Length: 196
Image (cartoon, rainbow, N blue to C red; front, side, top):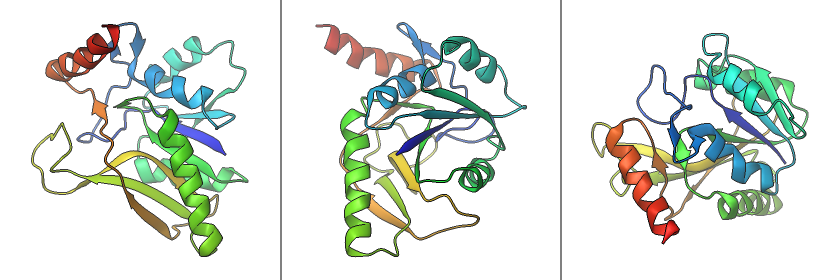
């Protein structure tokens, strides 16, 4: 599969313009996101950026100037579904969808999502997309309230023009997103734990 990392002022947090360039202990948010994906089952990483946000884009461009499997694309990323729609209309094969504000080792997640999705198609060919999400209530970082649902990591879509059947999977793995100072502290504590 191919992977899409859409960093263009969008992520799974609040809305408006999320900052994927928030760096923590050495790497920027997106860099932490992309690193596992690059080494994971997925071959090429297509990073979706927008003209409304090339700072993230100029960073990415600069960070991965030696890009072997890193591909930077320009699209509607200002709008989450707008981007997805553009991307689904340009890819010839299924690709992974990610949020740039998710910090956690995705290596097992990537493999699990792809496998589970393929398993679903195997039994039910009609399924073209996969979504993994977790209840907001157990989610470690509620922006406003625990009402609602949030993606647990990565998403799978087929490359078509329009919306498609998407399956739902619930996991018990938590992600740490960075929006504010407390979040950095929260995330740095786990890194600190790994440092010990």
